[PDB]
Amino acid sequence: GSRRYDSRTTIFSPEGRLYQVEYALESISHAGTAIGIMASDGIVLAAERKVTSTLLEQDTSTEKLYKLNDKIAVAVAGLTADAEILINTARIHAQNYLKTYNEDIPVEILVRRLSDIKQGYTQHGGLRPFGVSFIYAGYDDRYGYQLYTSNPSGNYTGWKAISVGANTSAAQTLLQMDYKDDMKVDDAIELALKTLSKTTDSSALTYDRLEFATIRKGANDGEVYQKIFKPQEIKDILVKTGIT
Amino acid sequence: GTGYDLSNSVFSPDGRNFQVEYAVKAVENGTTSIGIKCNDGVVFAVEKLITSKLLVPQKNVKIQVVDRHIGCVYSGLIPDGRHLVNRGREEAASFKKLYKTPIPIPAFADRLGQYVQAHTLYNSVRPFGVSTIFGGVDKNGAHLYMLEPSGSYWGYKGAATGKGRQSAKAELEKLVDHHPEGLSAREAVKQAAKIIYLAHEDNKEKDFELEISWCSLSETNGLHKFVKGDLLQEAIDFAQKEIN
Amino acid sequence: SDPSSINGGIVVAMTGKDCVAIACDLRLGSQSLGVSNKFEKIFHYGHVFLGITGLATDVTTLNEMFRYKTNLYKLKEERAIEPETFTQLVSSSLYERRFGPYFVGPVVAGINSKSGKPFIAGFDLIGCIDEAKDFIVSGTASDQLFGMCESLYEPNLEPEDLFETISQALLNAADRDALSGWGAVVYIIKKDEVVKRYLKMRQD
Amino acid sequence: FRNNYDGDTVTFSPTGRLFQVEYALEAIKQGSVTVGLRSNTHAVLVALKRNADELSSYQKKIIKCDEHMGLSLAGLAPDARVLSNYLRQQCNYSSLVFNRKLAVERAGHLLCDKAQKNTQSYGGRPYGVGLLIIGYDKSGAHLLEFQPSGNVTELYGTAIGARSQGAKTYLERTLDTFIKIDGNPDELIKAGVEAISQSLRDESLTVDNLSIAIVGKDTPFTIYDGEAVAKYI
Amino acid sequence: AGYDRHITIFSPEGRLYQVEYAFKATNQTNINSLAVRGKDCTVVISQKKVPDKLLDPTTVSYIFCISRTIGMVVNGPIPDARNAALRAKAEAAEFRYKYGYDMPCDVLAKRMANLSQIYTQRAYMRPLGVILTFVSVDEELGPSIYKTDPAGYYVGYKATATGPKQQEITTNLENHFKKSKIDHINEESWEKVVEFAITHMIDALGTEFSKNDLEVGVATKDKFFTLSAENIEERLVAIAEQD
Amino acid sequence: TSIMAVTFKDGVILGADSRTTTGAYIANRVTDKLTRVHDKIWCCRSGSAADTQAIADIVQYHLELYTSQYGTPSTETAASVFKELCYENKDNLTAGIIVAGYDDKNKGEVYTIPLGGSVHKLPYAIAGSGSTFIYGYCDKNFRENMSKEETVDFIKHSLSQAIKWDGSSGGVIRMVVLTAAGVERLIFYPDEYEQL
Amino acid sequence: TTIVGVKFNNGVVIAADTRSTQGPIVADKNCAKLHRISPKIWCAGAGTAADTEAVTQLIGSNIELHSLYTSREPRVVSALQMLKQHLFKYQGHIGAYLIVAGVDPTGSHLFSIHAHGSTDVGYYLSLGSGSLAAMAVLESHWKQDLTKEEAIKLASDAIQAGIWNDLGSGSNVDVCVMEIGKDAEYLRNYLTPNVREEKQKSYKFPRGTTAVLKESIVNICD
Amino acid sequence: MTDRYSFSLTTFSPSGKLGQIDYALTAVKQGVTSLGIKATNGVVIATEKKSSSPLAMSETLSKVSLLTPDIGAVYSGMGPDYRVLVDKSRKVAHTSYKRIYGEYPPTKLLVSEVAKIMQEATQSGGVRPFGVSLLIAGHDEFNGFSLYQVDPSGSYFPWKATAIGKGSVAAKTFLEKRWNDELELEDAIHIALLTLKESVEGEFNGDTIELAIIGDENPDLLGYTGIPTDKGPRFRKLTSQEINDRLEAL
Ligand SMILES: *C(=O)[C@]1([C@@H](O)[C@@H]2C=CCCC2)NC(=O)[C@@H]2CCO[C@@]21C
Ligand SMILES: *C(=O)[C@]1([C@@H](O)[C@@H]2C=CCCC2)NC(=O)[C@@H]2CCO[C@@]21C
């Protein structure tokens, strides 16, 4: 029969761990690092582009920062193609919520839904899990600025600052070292770049190897604005913060 | 490596399908059965091993009819044989229902062929453990066929399978050479009785019961009928006589 | 009985010089009974405007549907939808319900952000696209609207002039329709800006 | 060898064998003995009921399928319930639709075909029980032997289960004798008990231990247990 | 791990052994065939070998009439061959019903190739151990030869050969065309094309043929048919009166 | 509509008017009601043009696949496929079909499939609104084993009468001759059959 | 509606009026009833506009995919088979009545399909409420071996019959010529015999004529 | 019967690798070299027609396929896998876009559709990943010209120029030397021909090379006239002759 070739992607190890989830997480640890830092007046998402070439078109590229809603974005660490599958369903769920209640979906509700989908591949179906980890940066009128994280297991948690992908241990220690509750978006933007700068497995940290986004509530307006920095914009902020 | 013979639809490095070949072993281990094409019909005969005096004589019939003009006999796993005839019967009913005319032997053969070939395409099923000799009379003549577990089949002048297939084939080849003009149904019945008796030597240890059936344009009106009473004994004798 | 004559209401769109206008009444009734004088029938997704007459529940449902669809479109296409494209989205969305249609009379209005060209279009309840260059009417007072428009309309009117024209067409047609009126709103649209004006009319 | 070709019914061994089927046949041999024999007027079923403890009952081994048909089981009881239930439906169908009693030979063909399906597909398992079917139809008395392999044979008499070979040789000997016990059920039944006791060894057939069933010419398939079989011990 | 050789999944070298072993099966019949295009016809020759004296020679064939216009010769075990023939016929009939015109040879080929590509990708379907050579005189393309393998690959040919001694026939034909400089047998009658076909079959295989050693199929405008033992004999005689 | 099929010495002939109406309007005055389902198996269509076309298209498909596997089909087999479709879908079809074919062993054969989906093999058959008017004529003038010329004449006269009385019939008379010699198409214009 | 098709010595031409109506009201004074199925296979539609339109695009889409898959030019008989089997399946509920023409590798063709799924072939055809006015003209002027120019004239005259004599038809004449060896040429508004006369007065209102209650700017930029 | 393979055939190894994807990529590596170069007013994609026999008719086998009138594809890897992927891509451009918006999809979105199809063969039950890498070139009103690469994992990325297959490493290097953001279409075609030469062992002419471009609109390739807004396809495969003319100025 077929049984012979079934890897059994959803079973427990004698230690009570999920093989596939564990191996998927291992896969994620080799992915470009992504950072999420929450300030009092905004949120900062920064990611390091894994592998690059002189010929790679960066203006038309996006492999780590995706817009889910006009108030929610995610930073990706893992299989891009897997992330895109999940991102699209996340986008549909946000709209279903909007159409049903005529209110933008609360950040946690969207995260719990995406995580629940992941958890499914963990308990039934016999399919490999998604080799993906997300950092969610969003805003709603019940909790304001929020930062979340979800991994292959389907677990999610809230953070003031966090990272996923390669060298998270090093990144987390550096963040836990200089983070301060009363930070400001500009401060966080700088912290983020410094952290990546010290955890990169590459020579230097140039703009062509970064993606940047911020979710602020532009004082001169009263609404929330997401800003996915453009090549040139990253190049600028990279000089200003003193990394040239 | 190895293990190419554990799953049914697998190609071994030399391009073979071992399970189909092991199926053949089940066929060779079975009772011998034959078929003889005559000038206007076909004759079927088979060896019935008398396990004990407890078997009611003449009761456990092995030859089967399909529709009203086709006879089928087989060697190997009896149950697999019936399974195939059942399909053949549905196959024939369907054909008559749509086209009105009873199904032609060549058409009927391919129906059985495609079905058996189908059981060598997946590892979720097992090949048929029988070789089948079948045929009858139709719009243009008589037709004899033999179908192997591989789904392979061809039209025959004479055919045999099972324990004493070699003796049988040998006897059959003699008739083919000594009768380029064609054997008559009457003659084929006797000749058949002989071939089974002879071929019964490869199993001379157990006593047996002879069974014959035929389909002749002149002798049975093109309908498949069993040889019984006088005509039967007359053939049994013709054999018992030439067996010494 | 007629799903299109239960709630009442009208919508009209016109093309002018480098501009387009779309207007509607504000009534929502239940047969003879007036229920709401604030039921606006014009909506927009980016710079594309959509008016919808017919069964109110469907007007509401369709708006929610097109918001939903234009939102995902923006997320994937990374640009706002255009009048011509939206028009095709409306058409195929309605036809998809060919044998259980929404009882509405949609009207699209807008200016192509890249060509600057003005655009209006109408649809029957099963999506058939009517792409006129002058005007498009819809609702329980559509006959009256055709009469008003055919006479009052002339090509290349300036924004300020088209406003007067479209407003007079809407107003006088609504006053000959038992199921229309109770307020009106007119949208004057240009490449860069869009002005929305509420009109003063009979309340009977 | 075997170990690599006996993991499921869908696999042929290198010699053309079906081990799962054979392992099923083994469950029968481990089952209590039961006998069947017929004359020209009647058919009888004699079965040795087996008990767990001396505080337990002797599991029933005979099932009535219709007024003219019934069987005895050796092996997995649950599988006999399934197969007999299917035989009950088939007999019922023949009656309701064609107002015809199902031929014993036809029942045999139906059992064979149902058993066969469970020996060619992945996922299932062969039935692990043997059956002896007796019945009186339009062609007289009949006795059938059903093997999980799907092989069904018509006989004058036979036995299946542990030490069944004893009774089987006895019958193969007594043949010319009992086959003529026409018009005398008691004589046929006694001959049945004499064949079955040829497979004893452990104990001796007692009252709550012996089970007999008969069917024939003017006798609807009926089952006798306990006191009712006392006059045969 | 070692099962990457039982089902159709990649081996560490990016190979699909099951497809490779399927190719192996195609030579199991030890039969060779070749096809050539005429000026307005297409011919396919295939060795016919009937070992058993108990067989009815008339029922032994690896050539099939798929449609009124399409013929197909199969190199491989007969059961898989007949499975491919039935499917092709069904496919050919449906195409006509749905699109209102006869399915072109190249299209039927692509369709069968795609079906094969699938057994190459889905684990529950085994590939068929056969090579299909389709021929006809397409109403748009003219004489056509398209062949498909267990890999789901297919392409058109000026001429082609298939079987154990494929390479010999192929180089033989290649040479002839390097010489003639045209991509077809410049003959007006299919009879002569059939003769050319059989002739080179002999030269390349270095063997003589009787009327029962061959099997021939011809495709012309609006029709494809197979020749009889006698139609062949007449062919063998003609070639004899030249050597 | 007026259609008929007549068997004769050398085979069989099919005939029909060329009119399709939508009320009193003649939507088509040159319609071809003689449809080919196989080389020597044709049918006459009456009732719904849409239904009969769909039915025929399917029979042709079925016979094509039949040929691919079992060779040329018998006229009886073609009639059986038509029957299957008409009987099994009697609730949704309005199709009166006459099947006519030429076999070498059987020569000409005619099977008529009326509304309910029943099949009737006959020496000849007529159908369609116009047929009612020529029942008496045909019954009086039909003869078995007529020559090709006589048969063409019988059909020509019969149909011209049907066309004469039935407003639902008209245009030209089309015929299809099915014999061992092949397939012949015949057409007859108003100026010829009207004054017969 | 008035739509016609007319074959000529080396191709086919189809034409149609430009009136669109809702009951007795003219909704579109210049709609387009000529749709394309493939570059050289065009359709003229009558009946339910949404249906003729939707059906032309569905089969057109599939015809494109079929073309790409078979590496061949689409054939008229293919669009015809796909259209009729689709319409038949829907038992006339898809109110599409079409005249389908075009040129392909096998020649030039002219057919008609009805909502229920039946098809017809001819040298000249017409459908729609103008059907009878058009046909009257065709039965009066058609002849075999028409030149491209004659066919255009004939077809164009047939629609005029409908425009003038049928209330269900009006405005302009659209034509499309498909010639065996060339590109198909779509002639939108080939004839415009119904231009509206200059109005007797201008109804331009003096600004400020309309009473306004409230005014505001609408935000379009996100 | 019935596909009973409802579990993934591509799973994570302890190292975190996805075996079947890796192997699929290896298959891509053995495939004939193919490339794409973006110019300021067009895009060129090209590959070698590795005729598997001289009796084969190389024209009857296009490695360069038109997906939409403004989008084309080329690949490196398993030809049969590519063929079905093209059929599926042409259809999805319709079903998921043209039948909804009445226009063809923009290059990034169609690419995204193809990528999804490939990602699924990486996770769905009973299948193996596609053994190919595609280079898709196209144009659309709001994005201009673009070039994308899609690998077995389903991942895709935009390029100015790149190569895949056999000598991808060498070719990519040669491209980095000659590419600038001021190349005209003809320049890219030239550079493309040079790059491809280094990867070809034998004959190098318009019958052994396959090359197409996404450029201006070809009204002459529309098939009809009469609709101002319809100007023709931007995709155009070059002819054998057209290639040779450019090879002389090599
Ligand atoms: C004839 O039965 C008739 C034809 O229109 C029709 C057309 C083509 C083939 C089948 C026959 N059917 C009809 O409904 C009309 C009205 C009366 O009979 C018709 C002329
Ligand atoms: C014509 O048949 C007509 C058209 O409105 C319509 C419009 C576009 C394409 C199909 C044809 N159909 C109708 O229902 C109206 C009323 C009478 O005929 C129309 C004018």
Image: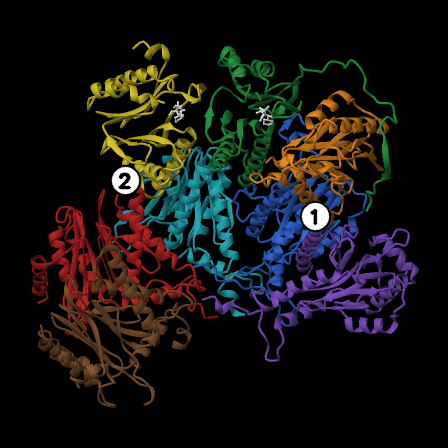
Q: Is residue A242 above or below residue F112?
A: below
Q: Are marks 1 and 2 in contact (CB under 8 Å)?
A: no
Tell me if residue D136 can be seen: yes
Mark 2 chain:
E
Side (left or right) of E163 relative to B76: right
Quick one: which chain is cyan? E
Which of E96/E49 is in front? E96
According to the image, label 2 marks what residue? Answer: E230
Quick one: which chain is red? B
Which of C104/G34 is in front? C104
The amino acid beneath tag 1 is Tyr
Q: Residue G48 shows which numbered tag?
A: none
- Circle 2 crowding by C-alpha within 10 Å: few under 14, some 14–19, many from 20: few
Quick one: which chain is green? G
Palette colour of chain A: purple
In the image, residue B204 lies at what x, y percent? 17, 72
Palette colour of chain H: blue
- Circle 1 crowding by C-alpha within 10 Å: few under 14, some 14–19, many from 20: some
Palette colour of chain F: yellow
The amino acid beneath tag 2 is Glu
